[PDB]
Amino acid sequence: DVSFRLSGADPSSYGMFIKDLRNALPHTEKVYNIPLLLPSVSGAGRYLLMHLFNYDGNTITVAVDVTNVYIMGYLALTTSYFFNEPAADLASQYVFRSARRKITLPYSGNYERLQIAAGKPREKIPIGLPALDTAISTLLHYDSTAAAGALLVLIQTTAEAARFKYIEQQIQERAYRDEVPSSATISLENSWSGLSKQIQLAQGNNGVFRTPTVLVDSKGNRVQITNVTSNVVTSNIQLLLNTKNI
Amino acid sequence: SDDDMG
Ligand SMILES: *[C@@H]1O[C@H](CO)[C@@H](O[C@@H]2O[C@H](CO)[C@@H](O)[C@H](O)[C@H]2NC(C)=O)[C@H](O)[C@H]1NC(C)=O
Image (cartoon, rainbow over the protein chains, first blue to last red):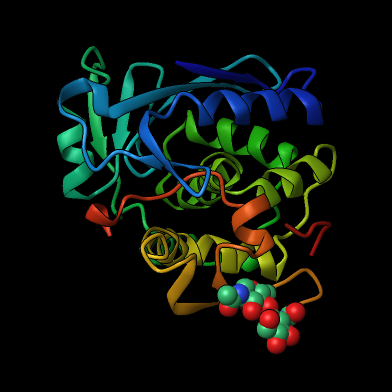
């Protein structure tokens, strides 16, 4: 398992947690020096448990699919909560077996459904370590509407920061003050699947992408990534979604 | 690759 405590959290201990989370994810090989996640894992080995502690020392345990870093559900006291999706229901027969009751959330775990449930696009939800502390607190008392918003913060500050160094650094900048995500952060989250696939099929093609990826950079300037030589590939992306799962 | 805020 991996653990992160918000009491006394600084940019450095957050960094150690994101590092722990990355090499908790199994891989057999690397493509251009970036860990390639497995096509599949059978049984209870498919899931990683993250224990998160808010400032007051309350806790939730979050289950993460190691093949794609998707959050499946979480345990808050004696209640487990799982997204309304086939993947999360498969997950429920392996993790949080000892929960007194299991609730299925009224949405799936994808950004689009989470945003509808929240009443806000993630452009307008501040993120940071303070937000994460809030998110943990919101999740131990069921409320489906607040939970959607708390899950949008949790996903971005854990899973997305693991996938990209840039996003990890964004969250480190927001250690003591929340701020909405930059445009770059959002386009990165949105392009993970696309970038993963183009990096993988660039490898018999001299590092050249079959189809260019369109991103937005820091200054909000539109950019075209065409090959593995770009900074995004050499100095940003930390995990690749296997093309089998794309 | 880039950084701060937004
Ligand atoms: C890999 O990506 C880089 C960065 O986008 C490409 O850089 C361009 O290279 C061409 C020809 O060498 C120049 O005409 C452009 O001005 C360069 N663009 C920039 C922004 O500097 C590079 O060409 C790509 N590599 C390959 C093999 O296509």
